[PDB]
Amino acid sequence: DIFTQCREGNAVAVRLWLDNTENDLNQGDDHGFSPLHWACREGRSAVVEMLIMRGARINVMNRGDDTPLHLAASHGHRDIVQKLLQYKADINAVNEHGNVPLHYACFWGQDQVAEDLVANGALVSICNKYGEMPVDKAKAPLRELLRERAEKMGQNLNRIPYKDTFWK
Amino acid sequence: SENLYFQGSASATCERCKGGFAPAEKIVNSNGELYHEQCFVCAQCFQQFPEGLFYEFEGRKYCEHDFQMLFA
Ligand SMILES: [Zn+2]
Ligand SMILES: [Zn+2]
Image 1 (cartoon, each protein chain N blue to C red):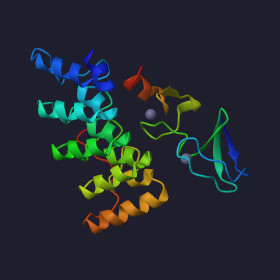
Image 2 (spheres, protein in one colour):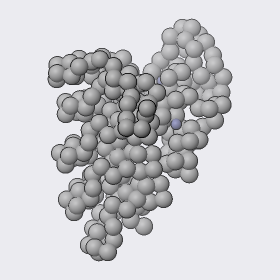
Image 3 (cartoon, rainbow over the protein chains, first blue to last red):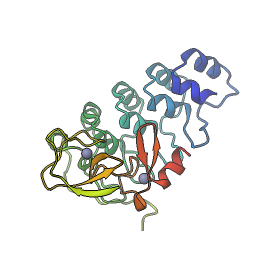
């Protein structure tokens, strides 16, 4: 199906599927992963660009409320992260755990993605639902570097406890 | 899995993050793989596995809740 073709990066098959406008390019699979989520997760750059340029919604969420930008960051796909940001992805989008894309880039040591996220304004001090800030998921060298870079970019380093509309 | 207090080889590395251990450090041994306490956690929520139970998907480990939400 379309989801497998996006995971595998079968660009011709994806293009032919998108040509049929009766197909819904935003529709998620059984766990809410859209074509764009899979292409971003698996680093399929050509398919990501095609989906975005043909109109795919950038901030779609899967069953765990991850966006394509969470998945690209978690799996270290630097070019895809930059493409998503260029096309207005919410850089501080939160999933069901209150995690932002920077949490995953930090946790997985995706250093260049984490640095690019902070260069584009990603907040370093926003706790998830369990009180953990993104940069505190990083190993020390990266953790220290990202706080310094954020300070130099005019962020405030005060810890921000989690809040959302339904929290209290 | 079991908690250990490290006094092993200088070559020893965490299965998740590939960093080394300090003498006396509380670590986890799961099936012969060694982890920092902060690394033997679910890849999605970063929290400890309830009762030590995890589920693998493509080389990462998940708690039951996140595994069922995303991959089951
Ligand atoms: Zn580790
Ligand atoms: Zn979890």
